[PDB]
Amino acid sequence: NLYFQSMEARVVGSELVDTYTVYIIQVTDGSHEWTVKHRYSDFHDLHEKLVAERKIDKNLLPPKKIIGKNSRSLVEKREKDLEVYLQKLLAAFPGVTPRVLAHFLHFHFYE
């Protein structure tokens, strides 16, 4: 069933090249350390999928999606807020990670 083991993640940066801020997430499973890139919408897709499958509380919520043009602003606060959310996600699944979360953590949004 659940066979992916525990992972740790931190938001270590972000970038805004085009339209949407992209977040840089450092991940480790104890064997390797790597980074993946995800946008807010990717976190929202992730979240909606976890809620629907009754794996997390509808109570826990990701950072509100920015309406309109993203700007290079409130970087520190946005990164921390995102990290708080992500680490709460991981703490909901001690020891063993749901397939969909493990997949999110291994591959960039554009892969």
Image (cartoon, helix red, strand yellow):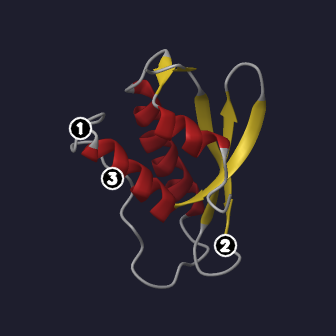
- State the SS at label 3: helix
Dot 3 amino acid type: Glu
- Residue at point 62%, 64% (across, down): 22
Instruction: Residue at the far front: name it.
Output: 1
- Residue at point 71%, 19% (across, down): 30
Q: Which residue is at the front of the view, 76 or 14?
A: 14
Q: Which residue is mark 1?
A: 57
- Residue at point 37%, 52% (across, down): 62
Kindly report which numbered mark, 3 or 1, lies closer to the viewer in this rendering.
Answer: 3
Is 8 on the left or on the right of 87, as rendered?
A: right
Residue 100, position as x, y percentages in the image:
48, 40
Up the image or down, 35 lies above or below 55; here it is below
Cα–Cα span, label 3 and label 2: 24 Å
Up the image or down, 27 lies above or below 77; here it is above
The numbered dot on residue 48 is 3
Instruction: Residue at the far top: name it.
Output: 95
Residue 110, position as x, y percentages in the image:
66, 63
Up the image or down, 61 lies above or below 72; here it is above
- State the SS at label 1: loop
- State the SS at label 2: loop
Mark 3, Cα crowd under 10 Å, few <14 / some 14-19 / many 20+, is some
Residue 42, position as x, y percentages in the image:
50, 59
Given contact means CB atoms under 8 Å apart, are the residues at marks 3 and 1 in contact? no
Q: Earlier in the sequence, mark 3 or mark 2?
A: 2
Q: Which residue is mark 2?
A: 16
